[PDB]
């Protein structure tokens, strides 16, 4: 019956606007298939369209804002786009209609409305671009009656093994079509919808902007050749209207020009389903999806005081929709260095110079192809899977739709190699690559990232212990199905656990280090003089110089997180021998955190290193790192150490700002130095961890209950209000917040773990 649930999940999730790297586009969860994308831009001159056209997501002066107002990947959503440069407010509605055997049908409305500043007669070019990859696939534009293009709908008829038969329609739409009185109109028509059907090698189909401009340039060349010149030029918009040439091919460009406001529909009808999808279907199903979104939001994200007001609701709906709306399907090769050069072992002083020499051998090669279904940090900047980010993304998503979350976890775990490594950054395919500077593309099999996906698994387990609607929770409602999922995933979790212990081992035995256990000690590979990217806390100060004898307290705590998860899942599956090993490791980590990491002098956990004189030294930089055993839930509610940690957390002159906890203490010598990435700013992911743990202590009999209750109440309020105020002023979720001013800074559109704020508001952990 697990198989039955699987098949239904497949069919439910198959279609989506799963191209979050562009403003609007669709693809199914199939590597080589049918994809769509939208382009638009004002044209006011003979050279401006190349500058105004929109396709891939950006953020700059020219774009006021954009995002999903509502979204569920099972149903669809509505997106808003505020384009200043092009003077347009755009709505893209997307809806899915179940039926047939190929994942069902879908429809989109594209609505553009000029803003108040735009000339009332602005000419806007709109393109709908369709490509299909596959060896045994076909797609064909049905030709027009009229001489020069289309008066009505453009109909494309296609077929593939993946999709069966289907028809994709781009409706006539509503709005003024400009008409040219020029001579050229005798040969090109006065102005109408046009279609060009082209073919290119499959691997370049994603390059829509270049493909389009190539056709425009061919058009212009034709003009010059046929004596259309500056003595009497056609209007710009006619110059950039493609000559109509529909047919078969693996690329179809549908182009319309509007003057003033416009709208039009895209209808994808799966043949194996009922009758074909209509505009009337679109309208009714859009209304229906909104009703269902509304009701689920109110159940799942019931915002508690003092955030129960309508303004906080709108805020919460926007943050959540942007997060879940960011879900993409990615397909293609990864760039991996599979040399396992010995320099990557980092057993020497100065290991970072050796490692750089090894990287400069460029042994990396493409491998796969792989696929991934994942949410993302950011559409305009980071539209791809990041390993420890996805842990935080899935916490709110799991509340919404646990089955969708387990799908994404499975997607991630299917990327794991036989060693137990999953690359921390998943750049699949040339499209995905196009956004990443070369320096940053190669993955290294010795680079870890925090195992945050285990947190999501813990939430699932507690829910398990204690048709779209049915499917969204099938995995907890049918305990047989939940256990089966765990049974299959469990070995991969164990493999990753063992991988951590093998590749991220620290060195106890080779120095003068006494501690309860000789095994438990950890060091992130991959550190440079100034960085430790693999830990997630890019530039958080660490022992100088980096050294093979370093030990990292955050890493040890992540291992504790993992082993606790394995005990809970192992128990469920009756893995007796496994549980007993995990139990000895938990016990060991618990003692060793104290023996190697706890500083009595400073009253917090510290990274460790090895002296000029080969002795163990604590290196203390008060900040998120210092709190880790607490953030990760490893300390007993009655612990004196916890006591000291709560004092640090609450201390205004260290970590506690009006706007949240500082990444680094104001008293640290590295406060606000260098790029100041994790050396003062307030980060929502770590604050979220603090908030959940504070609440944990507040809701249990114990000596710190009341202290925790106070800090929980204040921190919750500080974090939410900072995100909300910024969202109100700017439209944006930000990557981090300034603890002096509360201003959002770094990257916009970070939804992104900033979105955890909906979960903070709804509370009741
Ligand atoms: C300099 C640069 C430019 C562009 C670009 C130019 C035009 C469009 O894109 C893309 C990448 C890069 N540099 C790498 C990078 C930098 C920052 C992040 C965000 N972020 C940092 C956290 O510290 C991590 O914990 C977290 O996992 C992680 C993902 O959220 C991720 C990657």
Image (cartoon, rainbow, N blue to C red):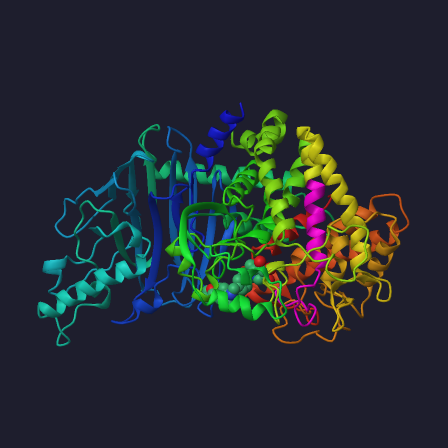
Against 718, residue 165 (above or below) is above
Quarter of the image that includes the C terminus = top right
* Residue 367, x across and y down, in percent: 41, 51
Which is nearer the eye, 497 or 517?
A: 517
Give the residue drawn at x 29%, y 48%: 131
Q: Residue furthest right?
A: 703
Left or right: residue 728 versus residue 89 is: right
> In terms of image quadrants, where is residue 538?
bottom right
Q: Residue furthest top?
A: 1
Which is nearer the eye, 310 or 138?
A: 138
Which is nearer the eye, 451 or 594?
A: 594
Left or right: residue 565 versus residue 117 is: right
* Residue 717, x across and y down, in percent: 74, 56
Give the residue drawn at x 44%, y 68%: 62
Against 187, residue 469 (above or below) is above
* Residue 218, x across and y down, in percent: 18, 63
Q: Residue furthest front?
A: 510
> In terms of image quadrants, where is residue 231?
bottom left
Res. 736 in view: yes
Which is nearer the eye, 277 or 436?
A: 436
Q: Is residue 680 magenta?
A: no
| Residue range highlighted in magenta | 538-565
Left or right: residue 664 versus residue 48 is: right
Q: Is residue 547 magenta?
A: yes
Res. 313 in view: no
- The number of callouts visible is 0
Give the residue drawn at x 19%, y 42%: 142
> In terms of image quadrants, where is residue 237?
bottom left
* Residue 400, x across and y down, in percent: 59, 40
């Amino acid at each position: 019956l697990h198989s039955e649930i699987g098949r239904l999940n497949n069919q439910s999730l198959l279609w989506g606007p799963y191209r979050p790297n562009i403003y609007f586009g669709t693809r199914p969860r199939i590597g080589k298939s049918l994809m769509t994308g939208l382009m638009w831009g004002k044209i006011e001159s003979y050279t401006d369209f190349q500058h105004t056209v929109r396709y891939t997501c950006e953020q700059n002066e020219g774009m006021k804002g954009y995002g999903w107002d509502e979204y569920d990947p099972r149903r669809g959503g509505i997106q808003s786009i505020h384009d200043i440069q092009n003077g347009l407010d755009i709505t893209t509605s997307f809806v899915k209609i179940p039926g047939g055997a190929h994942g069902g049908s879908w429809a989109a409305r594209i609505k553009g409305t000029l803003n108040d500043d735009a000339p009332k007669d602005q000419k806007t070019i709109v393109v709908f671009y369709v490509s299909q990859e596959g060896e045994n696939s076909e797609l064909e534009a049905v030709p027009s009656e009229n001489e020069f293009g289309y008066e009505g709908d453009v109909i494309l008829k296609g077929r593939s093994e993946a999709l069966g038969n289907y028809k994709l329609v781009v409706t006539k739409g509503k709005g003024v079509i400009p008409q040219s009185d020029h001579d050229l109109s005798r040969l090109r028509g006065p102005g109408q919808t046009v279609v060009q059907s082209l073919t290119y090698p499959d691997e370049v189909l994603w390059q829509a902007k270049p493909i389009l401009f190539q056709q425009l340039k061919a058009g212009i060349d034709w003009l010059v050749e046929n004596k259309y010149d500056v003595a009497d030029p056609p209007p710009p918009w006619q110059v950039y209207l493609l000559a109509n040439k529909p047919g078969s091919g693996n690329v179809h460009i549908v182009q319309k020009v509007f003057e003033g406001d416009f709208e039009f529909d895209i209808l994808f009808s799966s043949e194996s389903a009922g009758k074909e999808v209509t505009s009337k279907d679109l309208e009714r199903e859009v209304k229906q999806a909104t009703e269902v979104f509304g009701e689920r939001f109110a159940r799942v994200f019931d915002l508690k005081a003092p955030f129960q007001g309508d303004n906080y609701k709108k805020f919460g709906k926007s943050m959540f929709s942007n997060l879940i709306g960011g879900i993409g399907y990615f397909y293609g090769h990864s760039l991996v260095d599979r040399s396992y050069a010995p320099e990557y072992d980092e057993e020497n002083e100065g290991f970072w110079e050796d490692a750089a020499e090894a990287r400069a051998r460029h042994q990396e090669a493409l491998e796969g192809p792989y696929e991934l279904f994942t949410s993302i940090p950011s559409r305009p900047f980071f539209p791809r899977g990041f390993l420890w980010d996805e842990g935080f993304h899935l916490l709110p998503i799991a509340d919404w739709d646990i089955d969708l979350a387990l799908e994404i976890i499975k997607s991630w775990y299917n990327l794991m190699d036989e060693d137990g490594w999953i690359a921390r950054e998943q750049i699949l395919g040339a499209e995905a690559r196009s956004k990443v500077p070369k320096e940053f593309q190669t993955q290294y099999p010795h680079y870890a990232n925090p195992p945050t996906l285990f947190l999501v698994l813990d939430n699932f387990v507690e829910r398990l212990r204690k048709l779209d609607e049915t499917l969204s929770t099938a995995s907890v409602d049918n305990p047989e199905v939940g256990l089966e999922y765990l049974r299959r995933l469990y070995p991969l979790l164990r493999r990753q656990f063992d991988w951590f212990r093998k590749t991220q081992a620290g060195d106890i035995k080779s120095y003068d280090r006494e501690a309860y256990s000789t095994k438990e000690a950890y060091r992130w590979r991959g550190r440079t003089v100034s960085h430790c990217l693999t830990s997630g806390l890019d530039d958080y100060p660490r022992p100088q110089p980096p050294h093979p004898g370093e030990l990292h307290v955050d890493l040890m705590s992540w291992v504790g997180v993992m082993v606790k998860s394995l005990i809970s899942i192992g128990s469920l599956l009756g893995a007796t021998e496994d549980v007993e090993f995990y139990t000895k490791v938990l016990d060991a980590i618990e003692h060793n955190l104290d023996d190697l990491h706890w500083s009595e002098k400073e009253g917090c956990y510290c990274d460790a290193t090895i002296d000029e004189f080969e002795e163990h030294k604590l290196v203390c930089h008060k900040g998120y790192i210092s709190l880790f055993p607490f953030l990760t839930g490893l300390l007993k509610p009655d612990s004196p150490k916890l006591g000291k940690l709560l004092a640090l957390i609450g201390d205004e002159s260290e970590l506690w700002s009006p706007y949240g906890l500082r990444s680094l203490s104001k008293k640290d010598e590295f406060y606000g130095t260098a790029e100041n990435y994790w050396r003062s700013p307030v980060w929502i992911n770590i604050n979220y961890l603090a908030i959940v743990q504070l609440y944990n202590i507040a809701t249990q009999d114990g000596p710190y209950k009341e202290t925790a209750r106070d800090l929980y109440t204040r921190l919750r309020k500080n974090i939410v209000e900072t995100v909300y105020r910024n969202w109100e002023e700017t439209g944006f979720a930000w990557e981090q917040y300034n603890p002096e001013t509360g201003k959002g800074q770094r990257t916009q559109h970070f939804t992104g773990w900033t979105s955890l704020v909906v979960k903070i508001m709804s509370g009741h952990h």
